[PDB]
Length: 132
Image (cartoon, rainbow, N blue to C red; front, side, top):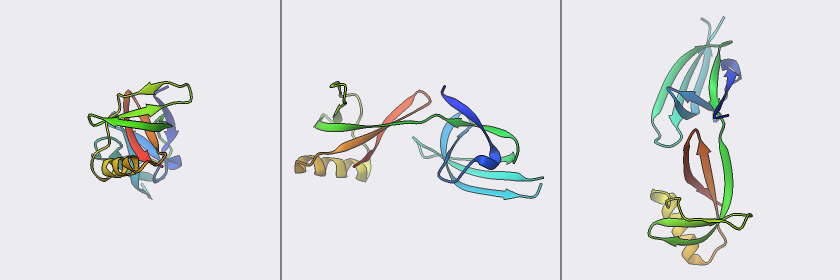
């Protein structure tokens, strides 16, 4: 299931919620006397866009079912990562992350270091989001 419902009061900072169809990470959450209301700020986990919403504390909201797996980096080519699974399958479809993360990944790869890359899926969407 792409998403599952959750009570507003149960939502948590650094947790996740779906806002206007987008999966977002909660960066600001306050609850005020309306009974009560939960004010949320969320950051689109892919584009970084800020979404906002004010929700009745006992009302539900949708939370994205985020998958997160770690692959082994065995190559970089034409800006694309060669990532290896336990299954033995190698995928070359995930782009090298932008900015510093990307530079970090290259430097450490050129280094000779055994690197794991975190891939993230949410809703129909996927990217490489971290290094270890």
